[PDB]
Amino acid sequence: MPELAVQKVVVHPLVLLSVVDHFNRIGKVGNQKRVVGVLLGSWQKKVLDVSNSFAVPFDEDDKDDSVWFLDHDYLENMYGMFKKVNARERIVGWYHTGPKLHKNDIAINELMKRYCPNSVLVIIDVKPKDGLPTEAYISVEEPTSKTFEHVTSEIGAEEAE
Amino acid sequence: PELAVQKVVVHPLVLLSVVDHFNRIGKVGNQKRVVGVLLGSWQKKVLDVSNSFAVPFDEDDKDDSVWFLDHDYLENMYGMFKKVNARERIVGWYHTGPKLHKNDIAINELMKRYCPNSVLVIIDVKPKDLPTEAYISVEEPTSKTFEHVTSEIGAEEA
């Protein structure tokens, strides 16, 4: 009875640790704002598996966030680089450090859909003193509007604390 | 201190980056060791290894003086890194050993192009197996070999 492409997202520690670092790592240079990135992983019985991830340069106007830019040439290259090394991981969605959805995530997601028709947004909460750290979403099409529904997301890679 | 570095702090990311990258390409009959670049910061002779990317690398299993590491890739990939991550620098390289290889001295020499005090870190990928073993090439005709540098893991938070 599944009208939805994905119904669960398993975000691996790497990713969460990837993003958290990437966030704080660029904070020592007065990083004020949220980070945006791409997710790479595999697909199963509607379980999306998010194995790996890279950051992409992204800007948005803090006064009208319909003014934003995400560098698709970068993402395409960087993903190209990834294929040269890591076996078949695919662009499976994207991420950003929220902590909440943004007015423009729907539009950002639309760009991403170019690379994965069932892109899944995962909002990775970067704050340490902060419920479950990932919150996956996926754009549903409800004139004909568009909005993000919640998809179950938990963390869980095999082997070693 | 006649030595550039005397300690290497390898962060969980790296260790987890590499281990994954290793096993992640194992599901496709990965037979061999992985080689890569380390990115990080420098202090009071403590090298801090914050981040790392894999580079395509091949070596002949019958004469490992026949090997190749793709420097165009590393330069590019690093280029991409600067575009995002703040000042991390190429600080050495890594490979999944588990032991030193005949050619690491040569591979290191290529790397020295990008970091005159490159530090090799052998990241042991096996679970039933300290997981990092940093080295640095010392120049002892005038030979060249790797000395051990203290390496531990330790990033702040969760």
Image (cartoon, coloured by chain):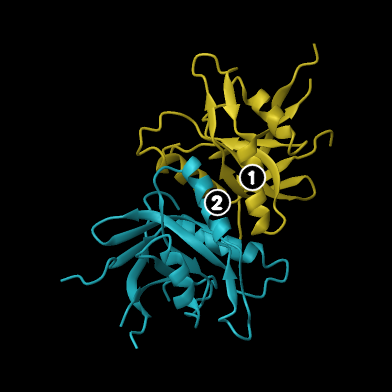
Chain colours: A cyan, B yellow
Q: Is the Cβ of the residue at disc 2 closer than 8 Å to that at disc 1? A: yes
Q: Residue furthest front?
A: A143
Extreme residue in the left direction: A1
The subunit carrying tag 2 is A
The front one of A95 and A26 is: A95
Looking at the image, residue B107 sits to the left or right of residue A126; the answer is right
Give the residue drawn at x 74%, y 34%: B113
Q: Residue at x 68, y 54 (%)?
A: B82
Q: Quadrant of residue B141?
A: top right
Q: Residue at x 64, y 45 (%)?
A: B76
| Element type at mark 1 | helix
Which residue is disc 1 drawn over?
Answer: B76
Q: CA distance from mark 2 to mark 1?
A: 10 Å
**How far across and how far down the image is residue B139, in percent?**
78, 23
Residue B112: x, y in percent?
73, 33
- Of the residues shown, which amino acid type is indicated by label 2? Asn
Q: Is residue A130 above or below residue B143?
A: below
Residue A79 relative to residue B78: left or right: left
**Dot 1, how many residues are within 10 Å of its Cα: few (below 14), some (14-19), or many (20+)?**
some
Residue B78 position in % (x across, y down): 65, 47
Tell if the residue under mark 2 belongs to the same chain as the one under mark 1: no
Residue for badge 2 = A77
For residue B129, above or below residue B144: below
Measured along the vertical axis of the image, is residue A111 above or below residue A44?
below
Left or right: A6, with B134 as reference point: left
Q: Which mark is residue A81?
A: none
Q: Please, what secondary structure does the residue beneath circle 2 have?
A: helix
Label 2 neighbour load within 10 Å: few <14, some 14-19, many 20+: some
Q: Which chain does the residue under circle 1 lie in?
A: B
